[PDB]
Image (cartoon, rainbow over all chains, first blue to last red):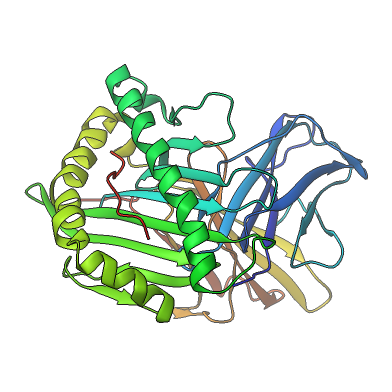
Length: 99
Length: 270
Length: 9
């Protein structure tokens, strides 16, 4: 009945510094559908962010793609902050250029 | 791959914040072409792929008319299921449906499916004979009786899946072949990320491929390292294609002993 | 093409 989201944070194309990319947070495997997803730049929220339209898997669990346009640099953190009724604190997953 | 047309409804009751949320979406294979969100300002079923934006107003109005009537039907299902389970109007609840068809050659239906879910678990399901129903608890047996006495399965679901569904899959296929029949092989590669004195993580990549189906397999000089391989779930790029990777931690050097191999459609060779 | 004419639950 109720399930925990899983998170993948990653760029669209392999992350080369200085060149523009899209950032991706893929959440999936949760139930029910109401879920909050912020994309973060050094702790701050990214505002211009759209997302894919609700869908679900064989086992009935929901998935969503939150994406925003950006430009990687040597210095900046990025990450994905996720909350959902199954969680007790928001879930932040950092962005690794190798994951 | 074995082509498919599929629809996904999601119905969620917001208490007591007015009206139930409804979302339908369509997929030809791994490509989304339509959506309807009962919260959009449009009040209309909308396109999501370029290749379907050629269809006339008759399509969209035809489609918009229909999916509003489905939305009302699901809205009342929320309160019937809430009644069957002795649940209160205070709780939020979800109903889910998926139906669709796998294309067989010669323009034949190969497989039809249609299946419901209440609060994440199964509920009722059309079986593969297109006549019977599988009902997973007391509640859904109430639901079953009502659809047996009406012939829902054979009279309206068999019929839909055996003709409209099939014909229209072939219509989306033809009207969008430049995209839904284009082989897109993965740009594929490996990278090494050291860990210590001993170890080094080898990571085989595979980006920009269509459809989502794929296999990434590490070999230890001929032998599959599964299941010593970390394989992340196939994930969307955002541009209609997909990406995956598998990782294996090896003792350095001894990574010349290791090779990755990728099976996918777009790696066609006659 | 969306299914329609669904018998209620």
